[PDB]
Image: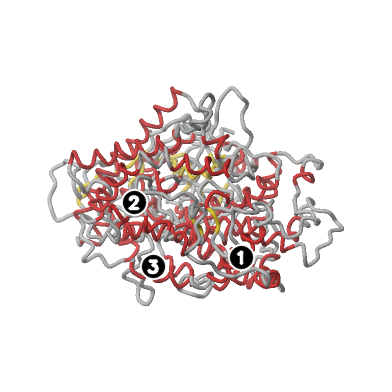
């Protein structure tokens, strides 16, 4: 019984920023979601369509573990049908999403005293995101009637702004490592159960 | 593609960015008020101009969006606090003169070096000195030197130095399309654009003049009682028909009358309510002062304190190896961090400010969801008023009955709360004309109502008509008598202390009517009643996004600033003050002079 690599999307060294969330296609193994929830090292865990009491019984073909890091009051935005700042320009879940987020507070290993400017988040965009879409771009957001040719001066602002992460903030703004688990079905034979 | 959407994306940049550079500035200032160090004082000045030269680059970029077409009122009240050019409206050499003269009036007030020519061998510092001599000195001439010399060596060098200040701060306001600098202090009470709730700047002078006319018989009957109770202390120094002398009001200028309680006590045979000898016997520490200050706040419905509050704050003075300046200020560092800073001791007047200081935080914890330029009070006198009502309910004998401090069998007769209400009369009522007169003098020297040679004749005549105070020495125009204060010399608005009083009892009229209190106001306790917390949290979370005249209608039911709840707080005092004043003469005359020799 070979365990699925959930040791590389939970206990990893560093996560990616929310504008460049890395999608890990976990397949050809046997999961044990139970471990996570049950030992409760982790915290919030909310699903729709599936539930953890029905998780280890029925199985899927490809589970998508999408890991990112956000702020404290922005964990509420990683939810179906939610609008805001992260949920409209960084990471939008579809209305028929069938997986659960797992968010645990990470002030011990992710925030540095006097500034952690290594995590970015998108603040402006020309339009909202389609579900499960990632835009890695640094093109300067035109918010005026003047075509700017790359310099971020007046009314032409840089799209990615930096998270500041001081240890001392608040549950309100501490770094929260968030990984979703998008389950889906195909014509391919289902692998991830046991 | 329109100016409303251009201002939303600019302010969305701004908030976020400001949060980063406001924390970085405020954390270096929190490390200065904990570790007074030469290495750490340059870190405050390096993080200070990085927010000052940031707000200068952001205000110029905020001036390209006109307010003539922005229609959403949240954006307009955000840009109104950013499109103000501030002190940068003048020229180069004229405005640097403003900055270098604030550093020579702030340093000359804190380091005023005055003493006596009779014995100049050993001299004085203001603290521990001239503030102590206004407390336990009951001599006439010994307090005359203590008050005249502070207005002859500190006010002397400010009188030709503040004439340049009034002609230079008018240029800071007449370039911002104001009438004078007096309209700039009145500009925070400005509300314009909302239907039915408008408030011009010129209506504030007519609103204080109508509220002061109603506390006129209340302050007068204190003045007929303080004068009658000072006749035995000084037999031939205070006339019964005249006004009070300046150098016997118990303070450095005459603002607060708290130090005049021990001479004019109504009932000294009964003990004053104190729990200082009750807290040390129960082994109460610095943590349990703020523990039970929180048990008042979670018991009204207001949110619990954050986990970062109990680990990053400073409550005990950390030894004699590092100096921590701990005059009690509540620090909003921003970004979810709400620390507190005071060297708290086990005394009652220290415990009573623990409820007041968390009221600054519980206000500031409520508008954390608001944008950054509106994370403030509804006006500049609104933050200090929402804190004092939390201290006003923690001083009642019914609240100390609950937390175990007071005795289980405690009597309370009709001669007990009169000694408590006079304690509140000498700190709140007696400062009400002294806040109005000093601000009426500032508004009538900024408007050009009195020139150079009349600059001080309409100060003591504003003293012996409004506050009932005659200065003992005939002063010429070479002294600037209001220049000897903390709030005049350091360039702060003073009308916030008048409006703090008329809000801190108007809110208590509204919360106690929601908490179902059957009795007078000074025995009311808003704790253990969550109906009054929700009537407060509907104002606490608004911040500056909603105007202040709708923050008052959301609580009390009146759009304006009323005065009848303050007079209703002192209703057992006003009845008792008329009972004892039959033998005295009410009112005063403008004729009496102690120097009429």
Instruction: Same chain for labels 1 and 3? Say yes or no.
Output: yes
Image coords of residue B110 (percent x, y): 45, 36
Which dot, 1 or 2, sits closer to the camera?
1
Residue B62 seen: yes
Q: CA distance from mark 3 to mark 2?
A: 46 Å
Q: Secondary structure at mark 1?
A: helix
Quadrant in the picture for residue B528: bottom right
Q: Is residue A125 left or right of residue B380?
A: left
Mark 3 Cα-neighbour bin, 10 Å: few <14, some 14–19, many ≥20: some
Q: CA distance from mark 1 to mark 3?
A: 29 Å
Image coords of residue B366 (percent x, y): 51, 56
Image coords of residue B248 (percent x, y): 58, 50
Find disc 3 in the rendering and name its residue. B204
Image quarter of the N terminus of chain B: bottom left
Image coords of residue B78 (percent x, y): 33, 57
State yes or no: discs 3 and 2 in contact (Cβ < 8 Å): no
User: What residue is drawn where x is 24% and y is 43%?
Assistant: B57
Find disc 1 in the rendering and name its residue. B224
State yes or no: discs 1 and 2 in contact (Cβ < 8 Å): no
Find disc 2 in the rendering and name its residue. A89
């Amino acid at each position: 019984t070979n365990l699925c690599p959930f040791d590389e999307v939970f206990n990893a060294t560093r996560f990616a920023s929310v504008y460049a969330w890395n999608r890990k296609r976990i397949s050809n193994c046997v999961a044990d979601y139970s471990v996570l929830y049950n030992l409760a090292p982790f915290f919030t865990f909310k699903c729709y369509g599936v539930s953890p009491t029905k998780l280890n019984d029925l199985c899927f073909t490809n589970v998508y573990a999408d890991s990112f890091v956000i702020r404290g009051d922005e964990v509420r935005q990683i939810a179906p049908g939610q609008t805001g700042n992260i949920a409209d320009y960084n990471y939008k879940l579809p209305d028929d999403f069938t997986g659960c987020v797992i968010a645990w507070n990470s002030n011990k290993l992710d925030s540095k005293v006097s500034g952690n400017y290594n995590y970015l988040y998108r603040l402006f965009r020309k339009s909202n995101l389609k579900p499960f879409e990632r835009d890695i771009s640094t093109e300067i957001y035109q918010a005026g009637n003047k075509p700017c040719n790359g310099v971020a001066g007046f009314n032409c602002y840089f799209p990615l702004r930096s998270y500041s992460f001081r240890p001392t903030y608040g549950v309100g703004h501490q770094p929260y490592r968030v990984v979703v688990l998008s389950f889906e079905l195909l014509h391919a034979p289902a692998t991830v159960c046991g | 593609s329109t100016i409303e959407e251009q201002a939303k994306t600019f302010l969305d940049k701004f908030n976020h960015e400001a949060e980063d550079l406001f924390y970085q500035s405020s954390l270096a200032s929190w490390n200065y008020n904990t570790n007074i160090t030469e290495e750490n004082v340059q870190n405050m000045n390096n993080a200070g101009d990085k927010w000052s030269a940031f707000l200068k680059e952001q205000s110029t970029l905020a001036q390209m969006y006109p307010l003539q077409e922005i229609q959403n009122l949240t954006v307009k009240l955000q840009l109104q606090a950013l499109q103000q050019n501030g002190s940068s409206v003048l020229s180069e050499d004229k405005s640097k003169r403003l900055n270098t003269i604030l550093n020579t009036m702030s340093t000359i007030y804190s380091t005023g070096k005055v003493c006596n020519p009779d014995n100049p061998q050993e001299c004085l510092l203001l603290e521990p000195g001239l503030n102590e001599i206004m407390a336990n000195s009951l001599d006439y001439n010994e307090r005359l030197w203590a008050w005249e010399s502070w207005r002859s060596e500190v006010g002397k060098q400010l009188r030709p130095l503040y004439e340049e200040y009034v002609v230079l701060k008018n240029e800071m306001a007449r370039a911002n399309h104001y009438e004078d600098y007096g309209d700039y202090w009145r500009g925070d009470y400005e509300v314009n654009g909302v239907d039915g709730y408008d408030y011009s700047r010129g209506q504030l002078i007519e609103d204080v003049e109508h509220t002061f006319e109603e506390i006129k018989p209340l302050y007068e009957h204190l003045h007929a009682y303080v004068r009658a109770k000072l006749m035995n202390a000084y037999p031939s120094y205070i006339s019964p028909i005249g006004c009070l002398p300046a150098h016997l009001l118990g303070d450095m200028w005459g603002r607060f009358w708290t130090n005049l309680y021990s001479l004019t006590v109504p009932f000294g045979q009964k003990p004053n309510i104190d729990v200082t000898d009750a807290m040390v016997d129960q082994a109460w520490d610095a943590q349990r002062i703020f523990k039970e200050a929180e048990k008042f706040f979670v018991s009204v419905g207001l949110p619990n304190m954050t986990q970062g509050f109990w680990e990053n704050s400073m409550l005990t003075d950390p030894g004699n190896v590092q100096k921590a300046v701990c005059h009690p200020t509540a620090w909003d560092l921003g970004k979810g961090d709400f620390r507190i800073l005071m060297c708290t001791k086990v005394t009652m007047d220290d415990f009573l400010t623990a409820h007041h200081e968390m009221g600054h935080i519980q206000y500031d914890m409520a508008y954390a969801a608001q944008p950054f330029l509106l994370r403030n009070g509804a006006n500049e006198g609104f933050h200090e008023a929402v804190g004092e009502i939390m201290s006003l309910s923690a001083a009642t004998p019914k609240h100390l009955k609950s937390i175990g401090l007071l005795s289980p069998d405690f009597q309370e007769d009709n001669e007990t709360e009169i000694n408590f209400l006079l304690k509140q009369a000498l700190t709140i009522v007696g400062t009400l004309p002294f806040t109005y007169m000093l601000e009426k003098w500032r508004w009538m020297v900024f408007k050009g109502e009195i020139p150079k040679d009349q600059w001080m004749k309409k100060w003591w005549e504003m003293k012996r008509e409004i506050v009932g105070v005659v200065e003992p020495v005939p002063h010429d125009e070479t002294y600037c008598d209001p220049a000897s204060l903390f709030h005049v010399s350091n360039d702060y608005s003073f009308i916030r202390y008048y409006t703090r009083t008329l809000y801190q009892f108007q809110f208590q009229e509204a919360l106690c009517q929601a908490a179902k209190h059957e009795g007078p106001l000074h025995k009311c306790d808003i704790s253990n009643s969550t109906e009054a917390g929700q009537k407060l949290f509907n104002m606490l979370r608004l911040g500056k996004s909603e105007p202040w005249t709708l923050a008052l209608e959301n609580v009390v039911g009146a759009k304006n600033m009323n005065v009848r709840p303050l007079l209703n707080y002192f209703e057992p005092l006003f009845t008792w003050l008329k009972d004892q004043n039959k033998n005295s003469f009410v009112g005063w005359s403008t004729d009496w002079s102690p120097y009429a020799d």
